[PDB]
Image (cartoon, rainbow, N blue to C red; front, top):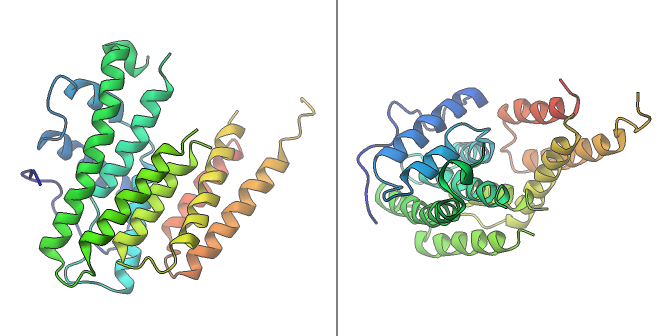
Length: 261
């Protein structure tokens, strides 16, 4: 596993942190991760262009799931999922690069470099997956069978990546499931977490479609779908004790999207 020089500093792993702090933390993680050697070659500029600035919400989901689960039980030195959250945003951003293709990513650099970049981000996302496993192996000796669980994570992210054409759901599935097994070597209720991620990604996509006196409803029907899926997701969350105070901020951000606020 090729190594870096530094990623994060002054981090309290299990502290209860709000979305903004989590966001600032992941931005420092992402920026530091560029520099220490991830995107070498002529595609150094493309990726950096694409990733810099964003909602970062999928990696944030990952990280909060892990920190919350680690509160419950620990395996010797709390797990702060950085390389894995990196990988989450990598996959999701590569999807975006591909979606914009025939300003944009392919505008400033060319469609050729655009797809070359997308492949680079997916590739080194898996590479940082393996890197997170290696970090776990060094600092977490009690962690249950890291090799098998890491292979299973790669397998699920695999199956999800090819099952994209909605297309917004699978990346949230990646975030949730990865954060679930990395917060705890469980695979005890992964399907429940699948329905949780699915409901949440559904509500997110619908809120995004709704984003702006035509009798066109206010598509109050679609809002009912959004809030119903959000309810069921919260039900699973508080059904596994990881429904923290972040999820309040997150749910209301989603809702305020659909409300025009």
